[PDB]
Amino acid sequence: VNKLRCDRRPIFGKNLIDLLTKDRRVKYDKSSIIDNELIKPLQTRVLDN
Amino acid sequence: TRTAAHTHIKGLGLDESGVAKRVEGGFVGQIEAREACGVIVDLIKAKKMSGRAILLAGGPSTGKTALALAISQELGPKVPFCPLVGSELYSVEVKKTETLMENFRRAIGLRIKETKEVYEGEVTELTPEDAENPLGGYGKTISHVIVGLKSAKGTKTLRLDPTIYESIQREKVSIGDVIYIEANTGAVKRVRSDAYATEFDLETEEYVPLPKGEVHKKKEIVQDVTLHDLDVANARPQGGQDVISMMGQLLKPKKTEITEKLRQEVNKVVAKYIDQGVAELIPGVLFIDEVNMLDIEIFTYLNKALESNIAPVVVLASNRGMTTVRGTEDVISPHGVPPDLIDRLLIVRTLPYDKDEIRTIIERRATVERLQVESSALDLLATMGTETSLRYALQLLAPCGILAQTSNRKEIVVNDVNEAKLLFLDAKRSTKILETSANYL
Amino acid sequence: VTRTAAHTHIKGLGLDESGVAKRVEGGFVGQIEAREACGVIVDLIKAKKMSGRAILLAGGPSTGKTALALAISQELGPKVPFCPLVGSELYSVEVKKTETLMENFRRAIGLRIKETKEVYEEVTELTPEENPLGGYGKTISHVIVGLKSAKGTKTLRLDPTIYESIQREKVSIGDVIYIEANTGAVKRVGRSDAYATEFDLETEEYVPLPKGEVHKKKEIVQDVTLHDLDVANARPQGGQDVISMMGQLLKPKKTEITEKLRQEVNKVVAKYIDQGVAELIPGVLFIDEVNMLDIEIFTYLNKALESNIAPVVVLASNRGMTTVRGTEDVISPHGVPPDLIDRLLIVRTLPYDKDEIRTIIERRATVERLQVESSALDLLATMGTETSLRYALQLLAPCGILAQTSNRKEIVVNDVNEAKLLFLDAKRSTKILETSANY
Amino acid sequence: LKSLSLIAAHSHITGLGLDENLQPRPTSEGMVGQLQARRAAGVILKMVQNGTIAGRAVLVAGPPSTGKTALAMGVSQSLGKDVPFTAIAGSEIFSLELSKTEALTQAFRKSIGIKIKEETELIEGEVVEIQIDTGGHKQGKLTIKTTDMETIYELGNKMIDGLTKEKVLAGDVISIDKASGKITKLGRSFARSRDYDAMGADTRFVQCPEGELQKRKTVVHTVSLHEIDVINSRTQGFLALFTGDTGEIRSEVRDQINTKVAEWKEEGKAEIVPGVLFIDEVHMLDIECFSFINRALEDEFAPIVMMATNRGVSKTRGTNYKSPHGLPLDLLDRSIIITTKSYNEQEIKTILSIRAQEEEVELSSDALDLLTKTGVETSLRYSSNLISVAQQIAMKRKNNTVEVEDVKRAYLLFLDSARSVKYVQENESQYIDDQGNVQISIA
Amino acid sequence: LKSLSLIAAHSHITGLGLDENLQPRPTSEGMVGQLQARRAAGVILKMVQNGTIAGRAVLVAGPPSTGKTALAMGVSQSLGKDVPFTAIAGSEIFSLELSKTEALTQAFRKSIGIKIKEETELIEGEVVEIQIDRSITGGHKQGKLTIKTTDMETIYELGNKMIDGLTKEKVLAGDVISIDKASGKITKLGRSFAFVQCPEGELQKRKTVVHTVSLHEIDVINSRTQGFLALFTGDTGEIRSEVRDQINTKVAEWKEEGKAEIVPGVLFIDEVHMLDIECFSFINRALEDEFAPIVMMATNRGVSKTRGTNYKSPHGLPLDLLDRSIIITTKSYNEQEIKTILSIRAQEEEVELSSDALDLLTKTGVETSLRYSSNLISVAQQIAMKRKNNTVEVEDVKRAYLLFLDSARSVKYVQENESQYIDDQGNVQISIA
Ligand SMILES: Nc1ncnc2c1ncn2[C@@H]1O[C@H](COP(=O)(O)OP(=O)(O)O)[C@@H](O)[C@H]1O
Ligand SMILES: Nc1ncnc2c1ncn2[C@@H]1O[C@H](COP(=O)(O)OP(=O)(O)O)[C@@H](O)[C@H]1O
Ligand SMILES: Nc1ncnc2c1ncn2[C@@H]1O[C@H](COP(=O)(O)OP(=O)(O)O)[C@@H](O)[C@H]1O
Ligand SMILES: Nc1ncnc2c1ncn2[C@@H]1O[C@H](COP(=O)(O)OP(=O)(O)O)[C@@H](O)[C@H]1O
Ligand SMILES: [Mg+2]
Ligand SMILES: [Mg+2]
Ligand SMILES: [Mg+2]
Ligand SMILES: [Mg+2]
């Protein structure tokens, strides 16, 4: 069980979740008030047509 | 502070009435080309024409790309500016025509600027106001909701339409933590606070400080988007657990040839919005260097594309003489550009340099690289540039500085440049070595 | 009732202890120098020191190059990997040829790993479970399970998680299961055989009871290749959500495996090797008709060979001074660019002679279980020396069929003549092709 | 021996053999001769280590088997780790999923890395023995113990709502951040090892952490620009860092990443480490690739580009004309050329001795002299392989040292290129001709 | 109303400029000269507007900068909206995900419109009262409203989906609302008080709406369940033939019964000289279909080599396609015509020109190409504006002429400085000494 634990514990990730969350963060909080009409994702287009 | 073949170029060094100074903005010589590019810049800033094409031609190492970079710098970061090498249009995923159209549309920009009224602050208290029912009834009737807001230096209580109650109910507003409401559209957004942050032993709820200034706020927000972003956002889906989202996530969504209908819809809605004064159009610049690598099909499609009414201004760079156009074998044209397209654009010449101009160029480049050279080596460097090439002399500066620093010196001398000549060769001496050797060299 | 295909009459290099090649041993005849060189090469491969050595065999058609390579593979042994390929096999459609070449390059070196595991194996009884005394709405502290096995029974206590795993397996009380305490996974082997005839029918196979001690300590040794680890990391099979399994549903197409993944795999393998858990064993990559390779793959071979864990590559070619395919004005020997042949070693294969051809025909007849006459064998040898060595070996079988038809067990001269008249060779077909109007 | 190399083609080289005044020593660190090229490579190494110069094209030119790849490997080794060094060949550019320019851009982005720092605070050592009994699971308190600290923390509604999910057995070392994030399970104390007889697949026994409960740490990660682009391209792009199917990342992502990196560097949270992009056999590459490089070399985020070629006045791929080194004059203009010369007899002997020392082969004096003679008449790599072949020959003979007889046997057992060419010329009929005419029949 | 646009190359022309009996005026609607070509274009426009003849191919041939593209643009402008006009280039057919025949079929089908009329009921007015009752923890809600016009005033009570439909867009007592019974779609016409006049007339009304869609869109919709998305993402591959075969018959029955009406359009192919022989053969076969629009192809090549072959043919097209085509030829421009073209182009860009400057521009467009002077107009105006005088003089025109080179001067400079540039063999001389 000692060897099992010593093998199980070191399973570190090559790219940690913290690193990718830091890299994928957005520095701008809120903007784009009039953008629910210019964008119009086609999921809404399916209903509109 | 990293320098790479540029960053000593800051504008065209122009002047009022459009006359170029001999030495200004990191530029020496090339007066006529700089004046023509300034006229082009003025035409761009006019924002009236569409699809105007200029091609600037000349020999290698004559400042052909520097001129385009200078006009991009003069135009300012606000306007779009799309650089492109002629070999990038050949994409495995999509046909070259659609890639050209995508880069063509990416140069057109749109600025969205609008104002918003905000009541943001820390909730003091909130209470419904009971009132007589408008109709016959037996029960409490709320006609207003009183909400008090306190921020740095400001405090104010407001009476609001009771129907907004659900907005609080959905927002889990609580009392005294945060609040941030829009004025006219209604609804509420919950942005805890530092006032009670240390009060609890530990909590997984974020805290924000007291908002600064008066509770009532006028905010002007401006952003810029290229039309290509609008097209790609309209075409691409978004959302959560919908089947289309799973399909997109599981398929590695390579680029697709966006239909013309979506582009027309985007154009119509954008025109409607700019009719209301909330949006503005900003034509940009599409710079393509080494156009000799373009195929004849791309040239033919460019012929039609330049005649559209939403085309940007396209500038092209080439350094070829009488050459056969790629994709054919019997058409020989100037600059490797078919005559029909040549008839559609304006040529801008570009002349080589003189020895004194080369010396000034080398001195300026040495100054921008944090190096000290006296005339006794600067003259030798100028002679090297006139003998081998200008770019060779420009490249040889850094090894000379490193060699000087190795000998615990500060100033570049004749010995350092001679040693750099011995160590690093130019093209001519390399070819001479190749020809005189017969050992697969 | 054993099948044969142009081989299986060779089973080694026929070398003594000192490396001297006997004239007729291991199915080979002649080719003493080539056999000695190949034995030296296989000794170097067994030395397990070098990395990236390259051997190329040169000779005319039907001279023994492929036989030599197969003899090397047989001499090496089943454990050491031996990846054979044809030159045209690299031109894939799903992925670029360089990626396929690298994948086959990594498929050649192997790794033997070992791991020691404990296991428990008839279920007697099980009890699930204390007071919450906190935020536990439903508490199952521990589960007691008893197993019977054959060499005595035993009971034990185990975590709630393995109990939920058992419930996922949904085993009964009179069953035999397979629980591996390393991963905490239970596998239902099945019902108990002695619990049969409870009902007149039962779909599930009853399966006998496990033999020996219930608590088994054991060790396992497996041989894999670095390409297996690369594939496992590139396309993991784990996952329970919709996305993972639906990705498993799509066809597996080769991609461009990154260099970083290979570097990390190498680091992990080196770390495990330093502990003595596993050991690596380089193999051999064999390529036929390298003249089918173009200049791009030939150039990439220079970079691949000078790597750090490159295996031993053996190349075959029968061309002379030819243009390297992919370029139009590069005359090179064997259709291999000058730098590559500068990077490798050359082994020449000599053409056979009449007596060697006769002995080869006799050996093929013996390994094919056929009876021939001395005069018939002499005629066959003269025929082979007149047209080709392969022609007689191919023509041997129809002669046997014709002999069997007339209830005669021995190949004779008239059967050989009839086979000659019935079946033509390349020379006669060429001589009768142009002497006609219609092609 | 951290790497998995058994013995490389050139593994005896560990950096350039030069000194403080950049003068190359005659033989050190596995390099012999090539003093001028070594000095130029040392100057290049100083330039790249300086980090104030972007986008330089240096081209190493010389006849085959003169040390170009060896020189680049020495430069990479002397540069040390922590600095990216992307080594590729020309033939790898042509891909079936990405265009040539896209692959070149990805290589350029991989060539330069960034160090990004991150400051964080954690709480560790949650050996608790919780105390929760009003209504709705009131009494929100729990203890926290470690080697030097011990204290009781009250709880809020959201904290207990987070705690009930991912239940803590009140005896397991757990971690939690004050960033209003998620409490992370770490492990179990050693006191609960004997309790069961078969642990699960997610339970480990970690010792009690020592020190203080509220720890603050800075962590620095080294990430290439290409990795950032890949991560930000898709929803889960990090997997494409292993599978490799990135699929022609668009320019908007690249410019957004450029702005983000500029902001990070301005705020002091990150710093850029430039690297070196090395290209073996640059002679075989399309005119489109050179056309793209001509402009990609001028970017601010451009590494130092080293190229290797061994061709004379040859035809450039994708064209009809012949140019020196198989490169257009436009690209050759914006580069500096380091030329390697042929090798001397004494240098060949020293290289052979070094390579034999690397393989633990004991050569006789006459054996080494004969090997040097053969490597002078023929190529050097032929003798370099002959040393190992002769070592195997001698080992088969039960003799540690290699003698002249073993070397001669190896020479007559494996054929040099010239002898094979002569044999092919003398026996043209037996081999398949360029027109597919062969004479299989011996008579 | 006007869509996004700027000053394009052909923004000054609006229609062919004809008389009532197809007689072309010398200068009208932005078109100057080329009377024969204009009358032929008018005849083709009448052919298209009649809507009886199908699958006619007409070829416009002439030297560069003559007016064929302008002729096609004028035809499209005079045809007006609601009539499809699909303009493509010769190089757009080549694709990596669609075969040449498939792309040509899509281009052909994109230029035929189908219009379906339907009748919709509406109830429009100003909201007078609204009472709404939500049962908390209850699954049903009780609604009622009172809606009036200038003449009528009536109350209604609502079901289930009416309440939520009214609540997603906040409806108050000061609003003007229009309701479609069939779809239940909310439409806010404005708040009367608390800038729109109160709705008048009857409380309910009827109207007709036309849905117009291309035949290619109908084809795409029925190909696959997800094919609707391909209407925007443009990702549809090789629609099966039976789909088109069935859709043609279905459209035929719809037209015969009277539900819908079809409108043929025009397919314009610019730079048609470059196209594979496969595309030419496919066009030869597909021109004969009954559901084929009028095809207008433009070319400027002489006896040139047709792509995909090794022999030269007139106009770059095979004789097979030329046999079943009608050719309209365009001729060069007189000096007076060039002056008029320059004048109208300058008038379009709101640029004031001097008479002597206009004459010099005419001379330089006679010696060089016309497009050169047309382009020079704007840069001359920019120079004049930078000189602070809002009038283009001869000096500004000469400054622009010397600053911006011409093709002939550039060719002469290259020929006399050959060593400066890179030749066809890749040999260049960068060193001055
Ligand atoms: N007038 C100038 N002022 C400053 N730098 C110049 C000037 N002319 C040329 N250069 C230098 O020449 C280089 C530009 O070369 P360029 O002529 O653009 O090559 P190509 O024409 O092949 O694109 C730049 O590094 C720039 O420093
Ligand atoms: N020395 C040999 N002893 C026995 N059989 C041989 C010998 N040389 C060649 N052969 C036989 O000749 C047959 C064909 O030769 P092969 O190796 O296919 O020629 P190639 O080298 O052109 O591929 C093989 O089946 C092999 O068994
Ligand atoms: N100065 C040197 N020091 C050590 N080894 C060298 C040196 N020069 C060449 N070599 C040997 O030559 C080989 C490299 O040959 P190289 O010149 O790189 O071939 P190519 O020119 O085809 O790339 C290596 O195996 C190395 O052992
Ligand atoms: N009759 C005309 N009326 C107005 N403008 C014309 C006329 N003919 C040619 N042009 C102008 O000449 C330019 C060249 O267009 P055109 O000749 O139609 O295309 P192409 O050069 O492909 O033949 C256009 O910008 C157009 O405005
Ligand atoms: Mg340039
Ligand atoms: Mg073979
Ligand atoms: Mg090399
Ligand atoms: Mg036209």
Image (cartoon, coloured by chain):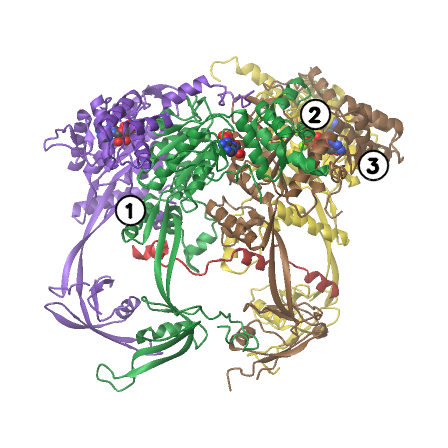
Chain colours: A red, B green, C yellow, D brown, E purple
Kind of residue at badge 1: Ile
The residue tagged 2 is C58
Whole-Å distance between the Cαs marked 2 and 1?
Answer: 65 Å
The local crowd at label 1, few if under 14, some if 14 to 19, many if 20 or more residues have their Cα within 10 Å, is some
Q: Work out whether residue B223 or residue E264 is closer to the camera in this orientation and state it.
A: B223
Q: Secondary structure at mark 1?
A: helix
Residue A48 x/y as whole percent: 30, 56
Whole-Å distance between the Cαs marked 3 and 1?
Answer: 78 Å
Question: Can residue B193 be seen here?
Answer: yes
- Give the quarter of the figure containing the C terminus of chain B: top right
The residue tagged 3 is D357
Identify the subunit bearing mark 3. Answer: D
Question: Can residue C306 be seen here?
Answer: no
Residue D110 x/y as whole percent: 58, 44
Kind of residue at badge 2: Ala
Q: Residue at x 68, y 38 (%)?
A: B410
The local crowd at label 3, few if under 14, some if 14 to 19, many if 20 or more residues have their Cα within 10 Å, is few
Residue D95 x/y as whole percent: 54, 38
Q: Secondary structure at mark 3?
A: helix
The residue tagged 1 is E218
The local crowd at label 2, few if under 14, some if 14 to 19, many if 20 or more residues have their Cα within 10 Å, is many
Q: Is residue C274 above or below residue D192?
A: above
Q: Quadrant of residue D218?
A: bottom right
Q: Which label sits in the foreground, 3 or 2? A: 3
Whole-Å distance between the Cαs marked 3 and 2?
Answer: 32 Å
Q: Residue at x 42, y 23 (%)?
A: B334
Residue D216 x/y as whole percent: 64, 65
Q: Quadrant of residue B434?
A: top right
Q: Give the label on residue B415, or none.
A: none
